[PDB]
Image (cartoon, rainbow, N blue to C red; front, side):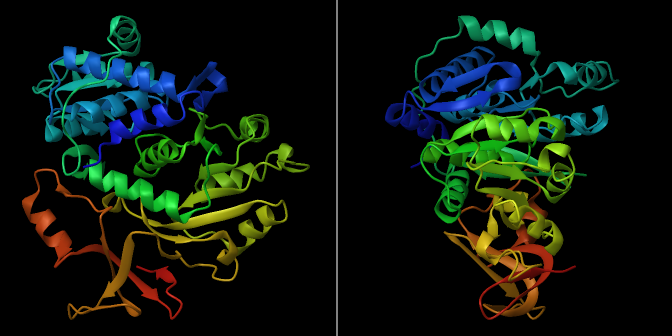
Length: 392
């Protein structure tokens, strides 16, 4: 069976001296050997807090090596990370903690106020035995052991619970996450030693899967914890970024800054845009800059995977969400229940990248699946070439 944590170890074994995480803004530059060691200390720290296989650890913090290593360490422990949107209000963060039954909550400085609020409410999440702040985690990490955990877990074992839209918790496994990373890596043109910019919050499925397939392929992560269009281009150029994760809104802003005028980044190949098709205009603007765009359709339920529109079709098939990625089958379910390859209907997905279930939501989990196919609740059309178009 596969284990996302073991994969980090295997990458540190194959490419120990290869850079894994580079965050200029914070002076952080680490190789895979060092990041795997930090992951082991994170696991040793979690274990000391009482975390055991299956227990949930909530992550409410800014992008950082620690954020990544904490979830990789949990992966080796067989624990379940619960990445939480740091922009939510105390009430919503509390509901997530109680609903998931998180045993330990690790939060960042900016989340101190929101946590103090929760710990001061009339009825706080009673499952939380520990509230670990940033500086507190920094100390535990210094003393922590860096040996490799010896827990036999992986495959179908829960790994992540990602809340989406009250919110439902999407539960992903080592195998669903492994499959999702593999789908990405085998579909887009990513290669050994590429340097990939991650400027989106890690609590999102897309960002999470990106961090993961990056380690799988030996990609160096270039981190911009706090997006800042005023400095993205310099970062892109300086760190020799090859690939960049982004959303249409972000790309729109970036083409505004004055550094875009005479922008010259020969190492940059393409941006990876999530959701909301790219307007034919914005694509041409980046094209007339030698910048390609890869976009697609994905759900938290499909671990950030689904369909992808390769750069070469970006203009020819404008508006399309692309075609099913490697290890993913996408079709349309008629209101009659019949699933067809082409035509219109509700978009359905059959792939190992799919969630195992919604957390403690038997009915929702049951209605989400139809004989092996996941019902997205989205209407769409699939043309003769297999291109998908999402509708209402």
